[PDB]
Amino acid sequence: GIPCGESCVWIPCISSAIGCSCKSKVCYRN
């Protein structure tokens, strides 16, 4: 539920591997 800080506006988040999901061009985690 909390944004990981990384945005997937054009390119997917690199730190997504920690459990981040792309939402509204922003990667969130829990």
Image (spheres, helix red, strand yellow):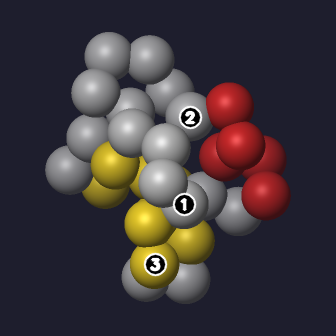
Identify the element where label 2 is drawn: loop
Residue labelled with disc 2: 13
Residue shown at 28%/27% (left/top)? 9
Q: SS for tag 3?
A: strand
- Whether residue 22 is visible to the viewer of this picture, yes or no, is no
- The type of residue carrying mark 1 is Cys
Q: Which residue is mark 1?
A: 4
Q: What is the count of numbered marks?
A: 3
Report which residue position mark 3 lands on: 2
Q: Amino acid at mark 2?
A: Cys
Q: Check if mark 2's residue and mark 1's residue have beta carbons within 8 Å.
A: yes
Vertical position of residue 4 compared to residue 7: above or below = below
Which corner quadrant holds the N terminus? bottom left
Circle 1 crowding by C-alpha within 10 Å: few under 14, some 14–19, many from 20: some
Q: Amino acid at mark 3?
A: Ile
**Above-or-below relation of 3 to 15:** below
- What percent of the width, then of the height, locates residue 17? 77, 47
